[PDB]
Image (tube, coloured by chain):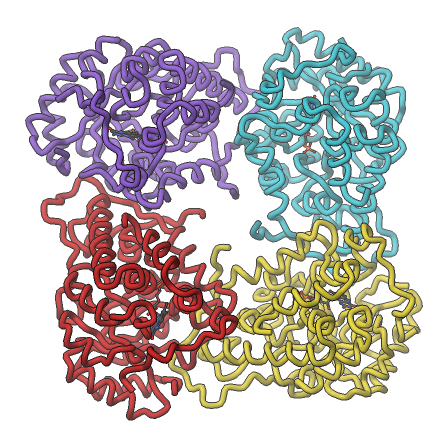
Chain colours: A cyan, B purple, C red, D yellow
C-alpha cells in the first residue's frame, strides 16, 4: 500500500455492499461528505526551506500523554462489522503505533476489553435518554484507564442516511452494542460530565465559533471541529473551513482537533497549518481493518507516519509546532 | 420515497415527454434554472450544538394563520396536466399537512372549488389586459376565503420556453383555464389591488433590493424573492443570491419568502438561515401529483416535514426563528 | 430557428471542415475564445419589476444614426467563404433589419458594391505597410457613404491559428481581397486617420483601461472592448471582464461597444447592464449566412431582435438607457 | 510541431511507460502538479495596443550574459533516460538558440563534457551528506565555465513519487550519475557556497515571501519560485500563485525566476506580466529530446521563441521589461 486510496479499493473488494455503504455514506444528498474533500483540496501549503531538519519529530503532547503523530483514531461504531477482531485489532495497531484510539459508546467489544489492550485509549460518549447510563459509562471508562472523554455533541439523533434506508441496513445478529436511546445533550449535560470526572472532556462536533468559545468557558479540554464525516446535517460546513477562525477565537484555551476527509500525511499538514493540534481519522482506519485486520491497520499507520514526516520535512518543519506556523493559500479545484 | 429526487424519477416515468418538459423547463438556455440549484449548493450552514430540543416546532405564523412548516405550495398553472384530480388533489394534501396552497389565476379547476377544499388557500393573481377581470378575480378569491393575494410581478408576458417551442406544446382539449391576455403590471396596478382588498398583498418575483424596499413602501404584506423558477428572464439572478441583502433592506417591514430549487428540508434550512420567512416549492409538488395523486403529494409533504424537523434539530434550532439566526458560509461546488 | 445555437448546428452541417475551422477557431490553445463564453455565463442580471412597458423600444442613436437594436454586425473577412453572395447577402439583411453592417478591409466583394446596398454601413480599417493604401481605403469608404471608420488596433499581425495551420488552410482561388501587408498601427496612425476624415473613428480591440482613456484623448468617437474573438493574443482577457471598468473610466467621453461571445438577446442585455452602448456579433451572423444566405441572416436578426425585446421587458426596461442602469451579480459556473 | 503539446504526444509514443512516468509524474496525489497548470490557466493578460513594435526583442540580460529569450532549460536529472545523446543534445540545442542550459548534479554525462559544448551553462547543486563533495562540485562547475550556481533548496530528500513506486522504477544500468546521499541544506549551506564561489548563487524552490527576502539578505543573485514541478511537497502552492507577492517583497534585490507548467510563449508572457525576470522550462524540453533528439529540442526552442515574440507583440511589448509592466486579471477555469 503506497496511499490510503489503495486501502479503500481493497476494502470495497471484500466487504458486503451494504456494510461498505454504512461505512462510506453520509446523510441526505451527501453534500457535506463531498465538501470535506473539496475543502481540503483547495488548501495549499506555503512551505519553508533551508531549516534544520536534523531531528524531525512528529510527536505531540496531548491530554497529558505523548502521541507519536498529531493524529488519533476517530470513534467509529460497530467495528466487528468490518473484521471479526473489530475494535481489538484496531486498538492493538494503534497502541503499537503510539496513536490514541477512541473507544466508542457503540463499540462491538466492551470498553473494558478494549482498554485492556493498553495504549492511549480515549472514550467517546453518547448522551442517553437515561442520563445515569451515560454517567455510568463515563465512570466505567475512567476506571478502565481511558485518558479523555470525547463527548459527541452533534448527534441529538442520527442523521438521515439514505444509503442505509435504501439498503434496509440492519446490524447482523453477530454484532451488538457490547457496552449495554439517544437524547439530545445540552450544555447542562456537559457540566454533569465535567463534574463526574477528572479526565479532560473533549467536545466533538463543534462548528460555530461561539460554540468553540463556549466550550472553553465550560471547561472543555479540547474540541473536535467536525461535521461528523458528513453523516449528520447535510449542508453543514466542513470543519476544515471553520478551523482557522475557531483556532483564533479560542486563542490557546483548549486543544482544537479537526476531522473529516483526512486521507494523507499532506492533509494532516494542511490541518496543522490551519491551526489544528491534531486530527482524527475515521473511514481509512476501517478500510485497513476490513482489508487486512490488525496488520492492515498497522500498515496504514506506518504509511501515515511516513507521509506526515515526509510532508513536514519538505515544508521545513522539524516539529508539529513549526507546522502550525506555516501559512496557507486557497487555490482553485 | 426517501428524497424528493425519488419523486422526479417517478414523474418522468409516467408523464408524456412534452408535459414533463412544460414542467421541468426554463427560458432560453436555462441558465437561471440551473443557477437556482447551483446557488443553493454553494451555501453551507454553520449549525449550533447543545441547545434545548425538547419541543422542536417547525410552525410559523404568516398572514395571520399558523402554518405547519415554513413552506407553501407555489402557484403552478394547469395542474390537470399532471393528474386528473389536478389542483383538488394538491389542495387536499396541503390542507391535511397544514401547508398553504396557492390557487393560480390559470388553475384548471375553478378557484371557488379549490377554496372549498378548505385549508389555508392563497390566491395568485396575473394582471390582465382587461383590468376589471383581474380585480374581479381578486374579489372572487376574497369571497371564497383566500387569505392572501400573491400578485405575480415578473410576467409582463411569458418568457421564451424553448422546450415548449421545440415540442409544439399546447394544452390538451381536456385542460382549460377554469376561472375564465397578460398585461404588464405596474406599481399602479399594485395600488389598485391594495385598495380593492383587505387581504395581505404579496409581490412574487422581486429580485432588486430597491424593488423590495418599494414593495414595503407600497403596503405589501410580503414579497417572494424569485426568478420564477428560471422560466422568465434567462440570466436573472437566483432569488437565493439576493435574499440576504433583501432581508436586511426591508428590516422586518414585510414577510420575505424565497423560491427556486428548494429540493429538501436542508434547502429550507438554508433559506431560513439566509433570512427567509418561508419558502415556496413548485416542481416537486407536481412530481408527487404526477407519480401518485393526492397520496403522492401527502407523502412528499410528510417527507419534507421530516427533513425540515431533522435539519432544524441537527442545527440546534427548536424554532424557525432560531433557524433564521443561523449563520452560513459560501463554499465551492 | 429558436436560438442562435440552432444556426451553428446548421452551418457545421453545410460548410467544409476547414472553412468551419477558419470561422470557429481562435489562437493558441483557444483559452481566450472559451473565456469569452465563460465570462458572459457568470454574469447575472438583477431585473426590475413593475415599470411601464407600454412602448418598449430597442433603438439607439449611434454615430449620428438611429439603429434598430444596440447591435452591429462585426467585421468578418472573406464572407464569400461562407455563401456565394458573401457580404452582399449579409449587408442586405442588415439593412432591412436596421442594424449597422461593418464592411471589412478584407471583404470578398468591393467596399463600394457593399456600400451601394444601402443601410448603415461602417468600414473596418487594417493599417498597411503601405500607409497610403490605408488612407486611400478610408477616403474610398467615406466617398461611398460609410458612416464610421472602425480602426482594428489589435492586429499588428495575425495571431497563431492552430486549426488553420493543422488544416493547411488557404483561400480558394474564387475568394479574393476585393478591395485590392499588415503593419503595426500606432497612436500616430490613429491621428493620421482622424485628420484624413470627418467620420467618427472607432478603435476596435481595446482592453486596457488606460488605452480606453487615451482613445478618448485621441479623439475617438468610440471603442470596441474586444479580444478579437479569441483570435489574437491567446490569454487576453475577455472584453466583457474589462467593460465595466472601461465604461467608468471614459465617463461618457466616447461610445463603448463590446464583442466576443454574444449569442442571445440575454447576452446583449448583460453587455448593456455592464455599460455597453452596443455590441458586435460575428460568428453567429456567418452561421446564418452559411445555413441560408440572405434569408438566414434575416431570420437571425429577427430572432435577436425578439430576444432583445423579450429580455429588456422581462428586466423592466422600456429603453436601452434603462437597461444600462441595471445592476448585475457575478455567480458561479 | 505547432504547439508544445504536439511534442508531449510524440514523446509518449516513443518512451517506455515507466520512463514517461518518471518524467510526467509528481508526488502524492499529484495535486501540486495539476495546480501548476490550473494556476496559469486562470491568469489573463490585459494587452496594450498601438505601441511601437518596430524592433521587438525577446532578449534579456541575466547573471551577466545576454539570453535570447526570458527562458532557461530547467535542471532535469538523467537525460540519457530520454535519448542516447542525453544532456549533450539538449545543451547543443540550447547553445544554438541562445538559451541558458542548467547542468544537473545528477547529469548522465559529466558536467565538464556538457560545459564543453559551450553556450551559457549554469550548474544546479544538490547538497550532499558529504559537504566537501558538494563544494567540490561547485569548484568543478566554476572551473568548467558555468556562469551561475542554481542551488536546489526544496529537496532535503526526494518526495514520494507514487508512479515510480508502483512501477518499481530504477535507472537502467546504462544510465548513471556521471559526476560521481542528499542532506538537508540550510542557510549555513548557502553561505558556504556563497563563500566558495564568485558566481551568482540562485536559490531554486522558494515559495514563502520571507524566504525570498532572506535569500536577498543572504546574498543570492536570484531565486526560482517553484514547487519543483509538483514532485516534492504534494499540496505545495504553485510558484505562479506566489510570484507577484515575492516580486514585490524583493523589490529588485535579486532576479526572480519562476517555473512549473510553462507550456507556451503565452505562458511566458503571463509569468513576465506577474513580474518574473525569466522562466525555467522542464518537461517540454525532455519531450522534444525524446521525440527527436537535438533537432527536436531545436524545433521546440524555435517554436517557443516564435510564440514569445508573437505574444509580446500582440500585447504591445517591444521588450521583456515592457511585458513586466503588463497587468493581469484572474478569471475562472
Ligand atoms: C461508520 C461510521 C461510524 C461512526 N460512528 C461514530 C460514533 O459512534 N461516534 C462519533 O462521535 N462519531 C462517529 N463517526 C464519525 C467519526 O468519528 C468521524 O467524525 C468521521 O468519520 C471523520 O471523518 P473521516 O471518516 O472522513 O475520517 C462515525 C463515522 C463513520 C464513518
Ligand atoms: C409548470 C409551472 C407553472 C407555473 N405557473 C406559474 C403561475 O401560473 N404563476 C406564478 O406566479 N408562478 C408560476 N410558476 C412559478 C412557480 O410559482 C415557482 O416560482 C417556481 O416553480 C419555483 O421554483 P421550483 O419549481 O424550483 O420549486 C410556475 C412554475 C412551473 C414549473
Ligand atoms: C472568421 C473571422 C474573421 C474576422 N475578421 C476580422 C477582421 O477582418 N477585422 C476585424 O477587426 N475583426 C475580425 N474578426 C473579429 C470580429 O470582428 C469579432 O471581434 C469577433 O468575431 C467577435 O466575436 P464573436 O465572433 O464571438 O461574436 C473576425 C472574426 C472571425 C470569426
Ligand atoms: C524528470 C525530472 C527531473 C528533475 N530533476 C531535477 C533536479 O535534478 N534538480 C532540480 O533542481 N530540479 C529537478 N527537476 C525540477 C525541474 O527543474 C523543474 O522545477 C520542473 O520540471 C519545472 O516544471 P515543468 O517540468 O513543469 O516545466 C526535475 C524535473 C523533472 C520532470
Residue for point 83% across, 59% down:
D157
Q: Quadrant of residue D139?
A: bottom right
Q: Position of residue D310 (x, y in %)?
A: 50, 78
Camera sees residue B248: no
Residue for point 44% across, 19% down:
B304
Q: Position of residue A66 (x, y in %)?
A: 84, 36
Horizontal side, residue D153 vs residue D262: left or right:
right
Ligand 2 quadrant assignment: top left
Residue for point 63% across, 37% down:
A250
Q: Position of residue D146 (x, y in %)?
A: 79, 84
Q: Nearer the viewer, residue C192 or D82?
A: D82
> Image height check: is B323 above or below A262?
above
Q: Quadrant of residue C182?
A: bottom left
Camera sees residue B252: yes
Q: Nearer the viewer, residue B154 or D290?
A: D290
Q: Quadrant of residue B263?
A: top left
Q: Position of residue D299 (x, y in %)?
A: 64, 79
> Image height check: is B144 above or below C188?
above
Q: Nearer the viewer, residue D2 or B147?
A: D2
Q: Nearer the viewer, residue D115 or D122?
A: D115
Q: How many marks?
A: 0
Residue for point 20% across, 77% down:
C200
Horizontal side, residue B205 vs residue A124: left or right:
left
Horizontal side, residue A44 vs residue B89: left or right:
right
> Image height check: is C147 above or below C12?
below
Amino acid at each position: 500500500y503506497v496511499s490510503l486510496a489503495d486501502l479503500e479499493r481493497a476494502a470495497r473488494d471484500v466487504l458486503p455492499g451494504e456494510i461498505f455503504d454504512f461505512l462510506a455514506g453520509g446523510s441526505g444528498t451527501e453534500a457535506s461528505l463531498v465538501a470535506n474533500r473539496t475543502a481540503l483540496e483547495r488548501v495549499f501549503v506555503i512551505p519553508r526551506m533551508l531549516r534544520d531538519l536534523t531531528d524531525v519529530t512528529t510527536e505531540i503532547d496531548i491530554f497529558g500523554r505523548r502521541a507519536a503523530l498529531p493524529m488519533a483514531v476517530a470513534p467509529v461504531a460497530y467495528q466487528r462489522l468490518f473484521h471479526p477482531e473489530g475494535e481489538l485489532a484496531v486498538a492493538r495497531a494503534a497502541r503499537d503505533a503510539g496513536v490514541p484510539y477512541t473507544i466508542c459508546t457503540l463499540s462491538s467489544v466492551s470498553l473494558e476489553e478494549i482498554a485492556a489492550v493498553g495504549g492511549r485509549p480515549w472514550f467517546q460518549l453518547f448522551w442517553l435518554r437515561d442520563e445515569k447510563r451515560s454517567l455510568d459509562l463515563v465512570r466505567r471508562a475512567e476506571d478502565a484507564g481511558c485518558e479523555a472523554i470525547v463527548f459527541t455533541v452533534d448527534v441529538p439523533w442520527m442523521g438521515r442516511r439514505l444509503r442505509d434506508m435504501r439498503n434496509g441496513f440492519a446490524l447482523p445478529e453477530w454484532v451488538t452494542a457490547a457496552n449495554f436511546e439517544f437524547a439530545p445533550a445540552t450544555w447542562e449535560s456537559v457540566e454533569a460530565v465535567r463534574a463526574h470526572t477528572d479526565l479532560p472532556v473533549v467536545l466533538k462536533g463543534i462548528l460555530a465559533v461561539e460554540d468553540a468559545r463556549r466550550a472553553v468557558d465550560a471547561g472543555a479540554g479540547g474540541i473536535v471541529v467536525s461535521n461528523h464525516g458528513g453523516r449528520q446535517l447535510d449542508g453543514a460546513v466542513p470543519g476544515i473551513e471553520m478551523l482557522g477562525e475557531i483556532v483564533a477565537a479560542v486563542s490557546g484555551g483548549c486543544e482544537v482537533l479537526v476531522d473529516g476527509g483526512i486521507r494523507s500525511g499532506g492533509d494532516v499538514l494542511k490541518a496543522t497549518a490551519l491551526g489544528a493540534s491534531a486530527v482524527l481519522v475515521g473511514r481509512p482506519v476501517m478500510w485497513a481493518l476490513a482489508a487486512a485486520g490488525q496488520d492492515g491497520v498497522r500498515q496504514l499507520l506506518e504509511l501515515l507516519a511516513e507521509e506526515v514526516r515526509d510532508a513536514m520535512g519538505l515544508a521545513g518543519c522539524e516539529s508539529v509546532g513549526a507546522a502550525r506556523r506555516l501559512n496557507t493559500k486557497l487555490g482553485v479545484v
